[PDB]
Image (cartoon, rainbow over all chains, first blue to last red; front, side, top):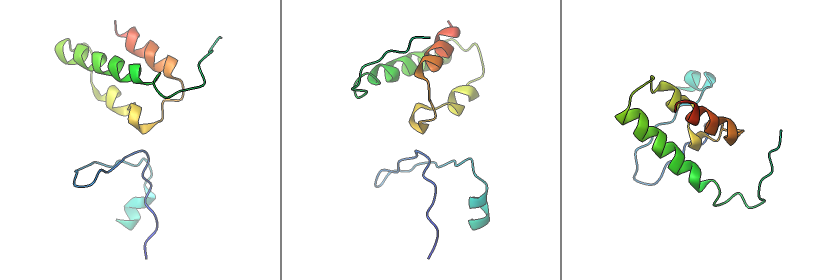
Length: 31
Length: 62
C-alpha cells in the first residue's frame, strides 16, 4: 500500500547491491 | 548545425562506453580536474540529450 518509487534509470539486478539517487525530495517524506 | 545520424541507434552508442572509459583512464592516471562532474553526468542516467556535447566536453579536457 505504497506509492511507486522513481527509478530514474537505476537498474537493480537480482542479488546485486545498487545505489539510487533521485533528484526529487518528496521521497524523503515517504522515508 | 548538422546532426545527421543513422536510424539504428543500437550499436553506435557502444563507442560511447569506450570513450568514457578512456576519459576515466586519463583522469585517474592524469588527474587534472575534480572527478565530481563525471559522476554528475552519467551515461546510464539517460540525461545525455546531445551526445555531441558530451564528446566535446570529454575532448575539451585534452
